Length: 253
DNA sequence: AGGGCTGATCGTGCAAAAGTCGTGCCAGCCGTCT
Ligand SMILES: Nc1ncnc2c1ncn2[C@@H]1O[C@H](COP(=O)(O)OP(=O)(O)O)[C@@H](O)[C@H]1O
Ligand SMILES: [Mg+2]
Image 1 (cartoon, rainbow, N blue to C red):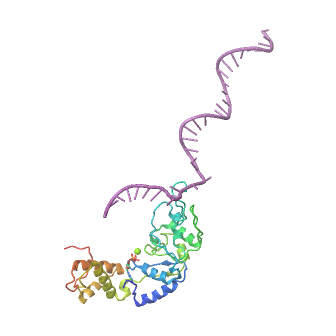
Image 2 (image 1 turned 30 degrees about the vertical axis):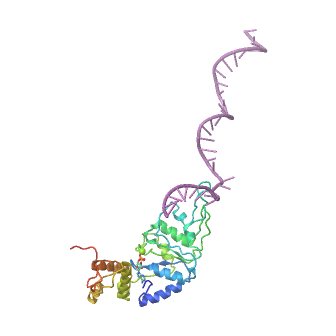
Image 3 (image 1 turned 90 degrees about the horizontal axis):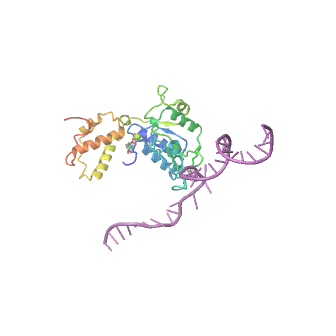
C-alpha cells in the first residue's frame, strides 16, 4: 500500500531495479509525469549495500547561494569571521551510499556539456575542505527525461548523452500499466480517510469506477491521487457509495 | 510557578589615516671675478 505494489511487468522491472541497486554504477532514470520514480529508487537504495551510506538526492537543481557547482563542494566561513570552513559540500553529502539527481530536465546546452564532461572526468575541490571526486558512489541521475535534450538534435548538449550510454529505465503510462489500479486507489482512499479521520469508506459504484477509468491518467498515480482527493472532498461524507469520481477540478456549474 | 539570558567557542587581512619619500627647486651667500 504505502509501498510499490507495481504491475506484473512493473514487478519484473522492480526486481531488475532492486538487483541493479547493488550495482553502484552511475545511472540516468526516467519516470512518468506522476508515476513517482523516486520511491522505487528509495526501495533500491535500501536494497543496495549503499543503504547504510548517505544518499543525498539532488534538490531539484536549487540555486541557493553563488557556489552553484562549487555548491557541490564549498567553504563555510573564514575563521576570522564566523565559523571554520568545516568542509561542507553538496557532492560530498551523499557519502558512502547513493547519490540521486533531480530536475535534470531544466538544464541548457552549456551545462549539459558540463555534465557530460563531469561524466567523462569529475573532480571535487573546495576552498573549504572538500574531497576528491571520480567516486560518485552509487550515482544515479533522474528527472532529465521531463525535458528531452537534442530530441531532434540541438536543444541541450545531448550528443554526448547519446555517446554516454549508461543504462536507462523507461516509464509506461498508468493507463498502460493495467495494475491493481482500483486497489491502489482504495489504498490511497483508506490512507486519506485515516488522515481525514473519516467515519468509513463511503463506498464506490463500480459504474463510477469504470467511468473514472475513462481517463488518460496523464498524471498517472499522481493524477489518480488528485482525482480521488477531489472526488472524496465532493463526497465529503462516509454515508453512501461514491457514484461520483472526480474528472477535473477545472469545470463550471 | 514562569522568564531570561547566558556564554561555553567562534585566529594569517587588510586597510586609514597618515605619514614620508621624490623631486624638484627658490633664496641667500659668499668665492670670484669682476
Ligand atoms: N507504485 C507506487 N507505489 C507507491 N507510490 C506510488 C506508486 N505510484 C505512484 N506513487 C505516488 O505518486 C506520487 C508521485 O509523485 P512524484 O514523485 O512527484 O511523481 P514523479 O516522480 O512522476 O514526479 C508519489 O508521491 C508516490 O507516493
Ligand atoms: Mg517529479
